[PDB]
């Protein structure tokens, strides 16, 4: 009847810990640093990482700053425990896709939204950018991906996860919704081995320059 946009539609389903960061989730949430972000923290005592209330976002930011320094031009990319942050290549990737609005970003995680938002906030993302993330955190990755895809067909669907079994869960969800091999780009890589800069150029290539 009228004009219709020819822009491609791209959906990303990505793990967080060990995919966007360089450390696996099991190696993140029981560390002293993660546990220090939970209300009632006592050193060398472990609290339920998922359901304990987190310290407020202002104090979380203060704890990141004391651990890593200010995230600026003086930042030490070689300091200890830098692998708990997003790599620079992953930060550049998310700055770009968190403004292409024909790209939808879904983080599918056993971690929790308050923590991931704190990591993004600490590494320089704005409140508007973080609000374009959808964080699916039930821990049941087939169910979360399947639910997100119910009901506008995507041109390309990205699936990224360092865990073989959670990757397979997400892929089964996407194939269950009728996406074929030409539309799927799945990446099962060990922590630190994802090619974020190449995925950024692959994404940019789908769109006009
Ligand atoms: Cl996970
Ligand atoms: Mg992971």
Image (cartoon, rainbow, N blue to C red):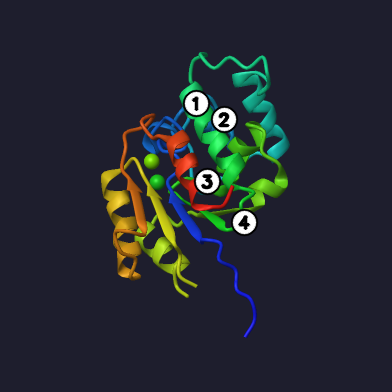
The label number, if any, that marks residue 204 in the structure image? 3
Sequence-wise, the earlier of marks 3 and 1 is 1
The vertical placement of 179 against 34, above or below, is below
Measure how far apart labels 3 and 1 are at the Cα level.
39 Å
Q: Is residue 129 left or right of residue 177?
A: right
Query: In the image, what residue occupies the spot 55% across and 55% down?
Result: 103
- Figure quarter occupied by ligand 2: top left
Marks 2 and 3, the one that precedes in the sequence: 2
How far is the residue under mark 2 from the one under mark 4?
A: 35 Å
In the image, residue 41 lies at what x, y percent?
A: 57, 32
Q: Residues within 10 Å of mark 2 (few under 14, many from 20)?
A: many
- Residue on which disc 1 sits: 32
Number of marks present in the image shown: 4
Looking at the rendered structure, which numbered label has been put on residue 36? 2
Q: Nearer the viewer, mark 4 or mark 3?
A: 3
Residue under label 4: 101
Whether the residue carrying mark 3 lies under 8 Å from ligand 2 is answered with no
Up/down of 204 relative to 103, above or below: above
Marks 1,2: beta carbons within 8 A:
yes
Task: Find residue 166 and report its horizontal and vertical position in percent.
Answer: 32, 50
Residue placed most toward the observer, 119 or 47: 119
Q: Residue at x 57, y 34 (%)?
A: 92
* Residue 113 in picture, x, y percent from top left: 56, 48
């Amino acid at each position: 009847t009228g004009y219709v946009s020819t822009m491609p539609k791209v959906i990303i389903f990505t793990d967080f810990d060990g995919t966007v960061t360089g450390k696996s989730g099991n190696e993140t949430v029981f560390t002293e640093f993660y546990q220090s972000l939970l209300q009632g923290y006592k050193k060398d005592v472990e609290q339920d990482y998922k359901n304990t209330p987190m310290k407020d976002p202002i104090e979380a930011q203060a704890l990141f700053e004391a651990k890593y320094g200010k995230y600026n031009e003086n930042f030490d990319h070689d300091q200890q425990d830098v692998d708990f942050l997003m790599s620079p290549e992953a930060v550049a990737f998310f700055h770009e896709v968190l403004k292409n609005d024909d790209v939808t970003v879904n983080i599918v995680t056993k971690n929790r939204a308050e923590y991931i938002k704190a990591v993004f906030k600490y590494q320089g993302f704005s409140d508007e950018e973080i609000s374009k993330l959808t964080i699916l955190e039930s821990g049941y990755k087939f169910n979360d991906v399947n639910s997100r895809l119910n009901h506008e067909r995507a041109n390309r669907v990205y699936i990224l996860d360092d865990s073989p079994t959670d990757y397979a869960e997400m892929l089964r969800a996407v194939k269950g919704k009728g996406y074929n091999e030409e539309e799927i780009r799945g990446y099962r890589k060990n922590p630190g081995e994802f090619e974020w800069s190449q995925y950024l150029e692959d994404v940019r290539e789908m769109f006009p320059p």
